[PDB]
Image 1 (cartoon, rainbow, N blue to C red):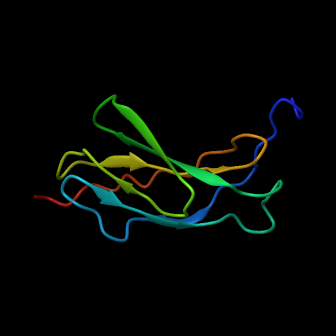
Image 2 (cartoon, helix red, strand yellow):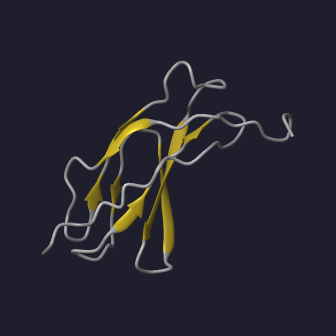
Length: 103
């Protein structure tokens, strides 16, 4: 329902890694276009998971960027992001599958 939970209807862009790592993986995206915004943003959720494994994990940060950790080297990692509003959560950005650097 609207009252119970509304959340945004749009996802951010420019989602990519500015400097991945064998174990860790940096990130850097941008906020949703003024057009696709059902209110205001407060934080984002970075959901990272190994497309090869069934281990799902995510993170939270009040910034348009983030840095994963505890990942395997030379392994594709499906990482995504999603904006959050005072109401709740919205859609989920398209994973990039940034494969950590080959140690």
